[PDB]
Length: 178
Ligand SMILES: [Zn+2]
Ligand SMILES: [Zn+2]
Ligand SMILES: [Zn+2]
Image (cartoon, protein in one colour):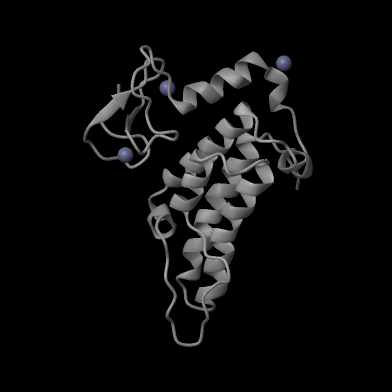
């Protein structure tokens, strides 16, 4: 197995996947690495299994159909994995914890949002459809763009949004377009 966490790229107390060489900190893995379960398969392996069981699940989909899906176990898992993919990028530190807003010439967003809040929400089964999760995710970046206006720091939002969106199109097999 790897000797660093797959998400944060640091060593520490790591849990090793039984079906692939990845390793995780307990709370870096999403969901948090399970207490017992020998063998244990990580989220990457669980997502691979879904594809393998139903190869046609990789044919193209319309985003509007994906968003209306109810959060049954497989969609729950896919949103967990997509969230995990954003945390995999070091630039996610900016959006992880609860933000605050005091900048001359700007007002804070009406509905603040952040990764750890989406993480809790998924854990607590607060989203009933994929749309719930994707809306909160996109709101993180939109709040950032609006607040930081013409400061160059706005680019961090564009950058982390692009990671989210690429992973969304991959995980949920959105039909490719020009
Ligand atoms: Zn980690
Ligand atoms: Zn694995
Ligand atoms: Zn099938």
